[PDB]
Length: 54
Length: 57
Ligand code: NA
Image (cartoon, rainbow over the protein chains, first blue to last red):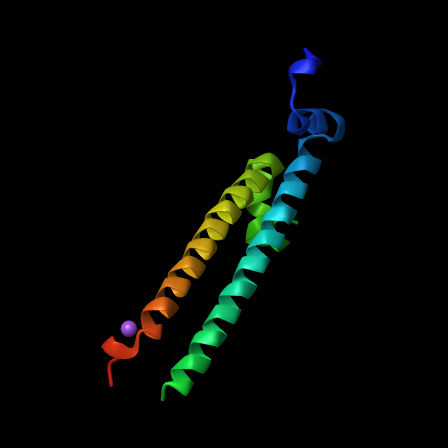
C-alpha cells in the first residue's frame, strides 16, 4: 500500500534509483567536503596556538 | 576500444553502475564518519593542550 511508504521510497518510485543514488552521493560529497574544510580550519587553529605557545 | 578504457570504466563494464555507485556510497559514508571522528579528536586534543601544565618543552 502506497500509504505505508515513506518519502524516501516514494521519491525512488518517481525518480528511479540512478537518480536517488546520485543525489545521495552528491550530498555525501557535500558533507565530506564541509567536514574536511572544518578539519583544515581546526589544524590551522592548532598550528597558530603551537606557534603562540612557542 | 577496451584497450583505451581506464580502470574505472573497466570496472563499470564488468560490474555495472548500480554496483559501482553503491561502492562509492559506502566509501563516502566511511570517509564522512572518519572525517567527523578525526575532527572530534582534534577538538579533544586542543582542550588537552590548553592545559599547559603538561606541556613538553
Ligand atoms: Na596539557
